[PDB]
Image (cartoon, rainbow, N blue to C red):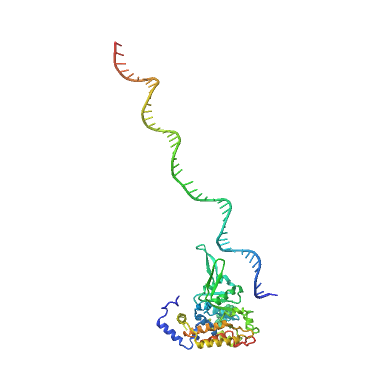
Amino acid sequence: DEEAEQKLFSEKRVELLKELSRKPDIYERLASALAPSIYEHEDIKKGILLQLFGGTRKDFSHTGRGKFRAEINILLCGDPGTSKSQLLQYVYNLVPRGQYTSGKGSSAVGLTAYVMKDPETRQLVLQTGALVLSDNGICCIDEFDKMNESTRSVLHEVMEQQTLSIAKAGIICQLNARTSVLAAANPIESQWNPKKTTIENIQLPHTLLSRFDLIFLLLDPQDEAYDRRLAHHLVALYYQLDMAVLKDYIAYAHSTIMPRLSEEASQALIEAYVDMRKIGSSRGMVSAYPRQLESLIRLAEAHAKVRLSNKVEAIDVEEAKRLHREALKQSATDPRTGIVDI
DNA sequence: TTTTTTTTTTTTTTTTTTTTTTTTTTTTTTTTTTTTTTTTTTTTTTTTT
Ligand SMILES: Nc1ncnc2c1ncn2[C@@H]1O[C@H](COP(=O)(O)OP(=O)(O)OP(=O)(O)O)[C@@H](O)[C@H]1O
Ligand SMILES: [Mg+2]
């Protein structure tokens, strides 16, 4: 409601925001402004920034196609203690219209909708669940893996078609569920073991993994230098970019910027999809489907929107590719087996 | 012994019927009683030779 309000920014504010957008590293600054208390998960924070910006809403209505999902769905898969729940908590406490779900505490009808009897009118009324209450926001699903397939099938239609068709006893409709999904999950065996391939170790239905457009592998390097740096950050946390500018920057980008693909961006996307499909066709890697091309499109549009660009260019597609590869650690992945360490 | 579908099964109600309980409610005649008449049976002041 605020972002749609025409006089939300003074001219001074708009000029300051545009001056920020001209900075070479506005992307990194805005990403680093997120979850400032979390130590160097720069790629996860960039992905979450892109999720907060989101892709370009499109009207495919005259194409027979249906509704295209402009939302970015991120999955954080990693061994415990790596601060996934802290990131989900930060996004939960930062966005309007968000929901937090964890594990077995949610059901399928508790995420979609159900009938209760309003105890002020003595009338049965329909109540929405977590996935509809975040219809234009982010639903944070924690312990994604410790969550039974009954309720995780509900996510398929939400993540593909942004709608929630319910055909119950009397009530038939299509609730809107245009949510972004930020999911955090543990590997099978709750700890990444290096003897198993990525697919064997994430252990999610392979159709469901294609719905996420970033899978960040939050793996622990047995690295002593990182141990020391993280230890200093955490201990320093026991004794001692603005937000308002970030807030207004994102609001301005949502209001005014509608990135459109340029011809050379189009070509970059074609090449990127073909290459990524060659790469992911290996043994136990997360494969690429035509849905990952749209993942790239969404990420590129979001990145162009970070620049206040209004035009998607090769740099946006390049950053989409890079983010997609860094998540999943595809540089550390051989085309035969799992990964090792960075 | 990790994952997974029938099975209830306790909890929300809703229906829903059958049964017991609840809620509502002045007018109209009649009759005794008192206070009057009214015909009749006395009875108490009138007068005569
Ligand atoms: N890189 C990091 N930056 C900041 N804090 C961290 C980092 N890694 C770990 N921590 C701290 O360690 C704790 C990790 O717990 P958290 O719930 O965030 O992890 P998690 O990934 O959800 O674990 P699990 O997979 O078991 O759910 C948090 O208190 C967090 O503050
Ligand atoms: Mg957690």
Residue located at (50% from left, 87% from top): A263
Q: Ligand 2 sits in which quadrant?
A: bottom right
The vertical placement of A114 against A255, above or below, is above
Between A338 and A275, the one lying in front of the other is A275
- Residue A177's x, y, as percent? 53, 74
Q: Can you say which quadrant of the picture contains the N terminus of chain A?
A: bottom left
- Residue A328's x, y, as percent? 59, 84
Residue A47 is at least partly visible in this image:
yes
Between A202 and A171, the one lying in front of the other is A171
Residue located at (44% from left, 86% from top): A19
Quadrant of residue A77 within the rendered picture: bottom right
Residue A320 shown left or right of residue B38 in the figure: right
Between A64 and B2, the one lying in front of the other is A64
Quadrant of residue A252 within the rendered picture: bottom left
Residue A107 is at least partly visible in this image:
no
Q: Can you say which quadrant of the picture contains the C terminus of chain A?
A: bottom right
- Residue A74's x, y, as percent? 55, 80
Residue located at (53% from left, 88% from top): A268
- Residue A105's x, y, as percent? 58, 72
- Number of marks present in the image shown: 0
Residue A166 shown left or right of residue B31 in the figure: right
